[PDB]
Length: 35
Length: 299
Ligand SMILES: *[C@@H]1O[C@H](CO)[C@@H](O)[C@H](O[C@H]2OC[C@@H](O)[C@H](O[C@H]3OC[C@@H](O)[C@H](O)[C@H]3O)[C@H]2O)[C@H]1O
Ligand SMILES: O=c1ccn([C@@H]2O[C@H](COP(=O)(O)OP(=O)(O)O)[C@@H](O)[C@H]2O)c(=O)[nH]1
Ligand SMILES: [Mn+2]
Image 1 (tube, rainbow over the protein chains, first blue to last red):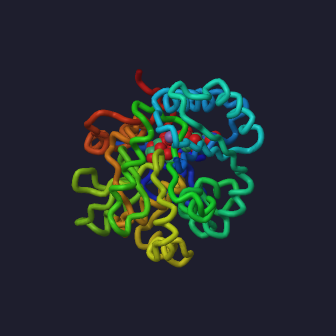
Image 2: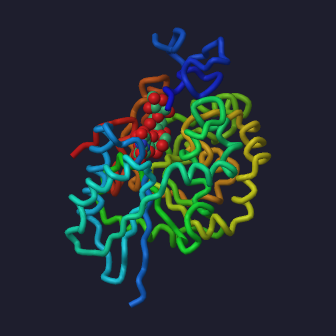
Image 3: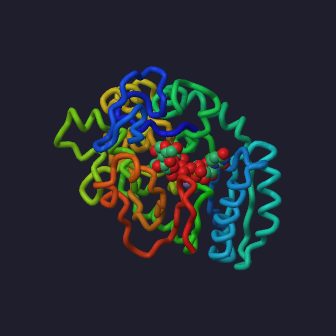
């Protein structure tokens, strides 16, 4: 299995090859909504 | 007497040298069998989907647990994951790209859709089967779950509990953004939070006999709905049932949360702090705990 994409856009798996933006749920920032 | 068969099905694959999975299975099967009670003419059939090494592991665990204290007749059946994968693929191929990690269509993902085509995989002498995860702990007599089949309304084919985290709130983001009045992805009581696949009542007869359910399995229907909902997942059967359940809730008998009380809080810590409790709340006497996302189960 994969880890869920924390981003609202793109595929369901984190680090989706076909995504270049990451839109985080509210209150989070970073390339994978880490902060 | 005329013997009455009860059927359960569990996935048990890649179990060799997977000690955490074996321990999960032990907890599930031991509590299941300790608390089960069946009449003298009744038989509990335990179906396992396993490759050969896992079949051997399951047999070693089962011999330590059978025959059950309660004394009832129990039969163990194994199904080859490779055989089922090949039977499932024609039916399930088109949905894989929307519901598997991630892209696109691999044989290795096919088995995660077993439930959706169970009515075509199991012998037709099996009218109903309950599919269960192995990271469960049973707090009651499994025989009691079978009475929920009697509560299916006309046209319902599957019994399933709601998903207790906002994972579908997240998944349906774009659809919700475009449809501000939608209940799709909202929490209970009034919303449609989606479904969890850990405990599923598959009425095989009803699934076979439903024209609606049959149509929804067709590639063009899968595609049209995944397009409408802008849906992408990696949770397999759970994702498919969740999606078609947004469009056609009549197909599903919603079990009360106490039949699959999920313990996973992953999503609480990934953007959903404020809404989390509205999804996660479950009140009542718990019948089955579900230690999903490797969550330790309380004692
Ligand atoms: C996102 O990725 C994280 C990290 O890998 C997962 O923990 C999340 O999955 C958890 O949260 C949502 C639940 O739906 C999920 O449990 C389901 O998994 C699929 C079915 O096989 C199973 O019966 C069901 O319990 C849980 O693991 C993921 O969304
Ligand atoms: O390597 C694996 C992974 C999963 N499973 C089965 O598939 C179910 C789903 O996985 P798990 O319950 O760990 O995931 P979650 O409930 O968090 O989705 C498990 O209960 C097992 O029955 C398995 O047999 N082998
Ligand atoms: Mn589980």
